[PDB]
Amino acid sequence: PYTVVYFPVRGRCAALRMLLADQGQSWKEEVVTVYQLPKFQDGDLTLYQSNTILRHLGRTLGLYGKDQQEAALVDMVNDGVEDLRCKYISLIYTNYEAGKDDYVKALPGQLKPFETLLSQNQGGKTFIVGDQISFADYNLLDLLLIHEVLAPGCLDAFPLLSAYVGRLSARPKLKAFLASPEYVNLPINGNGKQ
Amino acid sequence: PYTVVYFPVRGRCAALRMLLADQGQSWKEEVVTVYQLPKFQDGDLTLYQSNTILRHLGRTLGLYGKDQQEAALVDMVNDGVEDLRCKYISLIYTNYEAGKDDYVKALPGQLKPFETLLSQNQGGKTFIVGDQISFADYNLLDLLLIHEVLAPGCLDAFPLLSAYVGRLSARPKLKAFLASPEYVNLPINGNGKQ
Image (cartoon, rainbow over all chains, first blue to last red; front, top):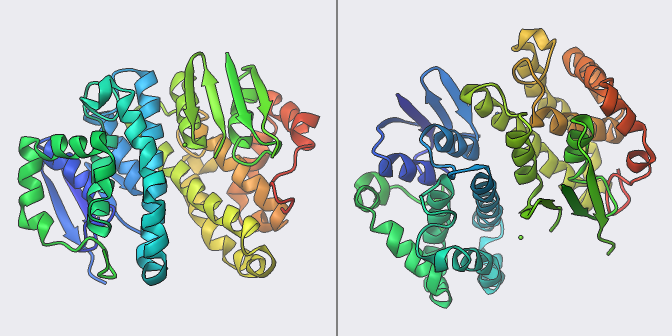
């Protein structure tokens, strides 16, 4: 019984959509043509804030680590992703024309921490945290994909990340969703820039 | 076995310090004179990001709601607080001189949601969520206190919030901590503005 209310763009819902899709859950979309959405309805539970939804789905669907220690790392990784996403959103809607240059120059410094974190966990052979997927993976994967569109090839300097994007992108239900019109035909951002 | 590494300012640690103080936990500070701190060490567990720490302490100290439903609301409230805190931080370090005017004009619109949320929970007679304190309370309380310093009297238009700040501020261990030199003598912000 899931319903997500959002604009007709992937934006901040791409991650939770991927999460739902991959976990084999069904939801109802509810477009909003022109607390800022998304809005999520789980039964009579009504959530706002994308990360709130991600954690909620994480708790209830068991994508929050195997113990309190991992849970903390998952949060820490998610917050980093979120931090970078804020810069991206700022670039897109604010200084896209001028900032794009400087942004890509700095991108490697922004992505290196993730590469490191990956190397520290079974040599990046599984997920960003632990040996099971978590909501932070779906969110990290989205951040990496939307960046490969802004600056194609940015992930070439990071062997672990690139393998990671490939590993996750190949997950049965996820691959299908990523290839669906439902995903492919939605613009990444509202202002039409990406 | 807690250690918090941060600058010599309350900044983003005020909340977790209040949390620790109120919960009767002891920690070791480690000043950093001139992932951006804080850094938290719980045993060999090393966390970064203030909210990550807040959730961690929330999970382990049982300040995360009584069930998954409340947990979600706690997150939702915390994210709202965090959203406003980002604006505050932006005012302080960026457009303080000019933005202060417009900021205070808009403040009521920013605080109204919290007043509402409060009224919806036992008529604001307990905490922001549920009938037990949660990490979001400590974080909300900090946000309200630092605002009463920026724009004194801003809470007069909201009876529920004002009672809330008074109710929590009177908590035995919290009142003491709020009166300690450890708290009182630390500047609110780095740039010396508040």
